[PDB]
Structures are given as C-alpha cells and as structure tokens.
Image (cartoon, rainbow, N blue to C red):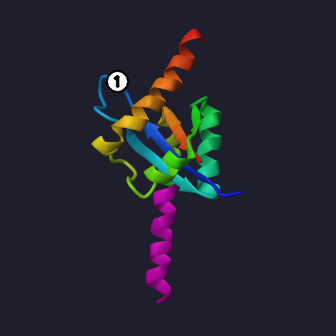
C-alpha cells in the first residue's frame, strides 16, 4: 500500500505551535509509526490532512499558523481520549 | 558525476538517521 506520516512534537508551555520532527513516505513512514508505536506515541489516521501537510512543512520547523486549525483539533482528540485512561 | 552524487546520497542518508532518532520525542503522528 501507499504510506505517509508526519511526526509532531508539542509542549504546551514551551512550543507556541507543533514542531515537525519527522516526515515520511514508504518504509520511512512505516518506521516512524513503528518507533512511535514503540514509544506509545499516538498515531492518527487523517489522510486528507497528512496529504495536505507533507509538502507544506519541513523537519525541525514549527507548522504554519494556517495549520493551527486541524492540528489543534487532533492534539485535542488525542488528549481527550487519554484523559479517562 | 559519481562522487558528487555519492556525497548527496550520504547526506540524504545522514539526514534520515537524525530524523528517525528524533521520533522518540514526538507527541503525535499524522498518518494516511
């Protein structure tokens, strides 16, 4: 199958926005997923977004203000789910 | 050219090891 992934680091006090720490196609993508699952880092399937996000940004640099809309929605879902346990 | 491209390849490769090592620091991954 086709494979893509975008890894993001975000602290609430230090980062104004999410830093792209990795982006990946094919076996690179799969590697990021695997290490992450390995670290119990959440993984979200959002294809129109992952697609739209890939060419847009680069490794080590905080996402565009434009993306704040869909990314923040995701960080939100991720964290709502993790609250109960 | 054989060498310039071998240098390029290797820089590509090195950039990738850095990147995959920085993944343990992620908080979220978006996937297709």
> Between residues A36 and A45, which one lies in front from this camera angle?
A45
Image quarter hosting the N terminus of chain A: bottom right
Farthest residue in the bottom direction?
B1
Q: Would residue A42 be found to the left or right of residue A53 on screen?
A: right
How many neighbours does mark 1 have within 10 angstroms: few (below 14), some (14-19), or many (20 or more)? few
Magenta: main secondary structure equals helix
Question: Regarding mark 1 in the picture, which secondary structure is present there?
Answer: loop
Q: In terms of depth relative to the viewer, which is nearer, A2 or A28?
A: A2
Query: Pointer 1: what residue?
Result: A12
Indicate the chain on which mark 1 is placed: A
Please say if A34 is above or below B6: above
Q: Looking at the picture, tell me which residue is in the foreground, B23 or A15.
A: A15
Where, by quadrant of the figure, is residue A65 drawn? top left
Q: Residue at x 52, y 25 (%)?
A: A78
Which image quarter: residue A11?
A: top left
- Magenta region: B1-16
Q: Position of residue A43 (x, y in %)?
A: 59, 35
Above or below: residue B16 compared with residue A80: below
Q: Residue at x 56, y 47 (%)?
A: A47
In this picture, residue A12 sits left or right of residue B32: left
Residue A10 lies in the magenta stretch: no
Residue shown at 46% from the left, 24% from the top: A76
Q: Percent position (x, y) of residue A58? A: 38, 53
* The C terminus of chain A sits in image quarter: top right
Q: Is residue A11 above or below residue B22?
A: above
Q: Residue B11 placed where, x, y %?
A: 45, 67
> Does B9 lie within the magenta span?
yes
Q: What residue is rendered at 54% in x and 54% in y?
A: A24
């Amino acid at each position: 199958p086709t494979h893509i992934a975008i890894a993001l680091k975000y602290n609430p006090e230090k980062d104004k926005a999410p830093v792209v720490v990795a982006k990946g196609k094919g076996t690179i993508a799969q590697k990021i997923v695997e290490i992450a699952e390995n670290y119990s880092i959440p993984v979200v399937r959002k294809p129109e977004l992952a697609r739209a996000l890939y060419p847009a940004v680069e490794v080590g640099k905080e996402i565009s203000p434009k993306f704040y809309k869909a990314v923040a929605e995701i960080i939100a879902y991720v964290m709502f789910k993790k609250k109960k346990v | 050219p054989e060498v310039k491209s071998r240098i390029k390849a290797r820089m590509r490769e090195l950039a990738k090891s850095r990147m995959m090592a920085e993944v343990p620091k992620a908080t979220v991954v978006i996937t297709n």
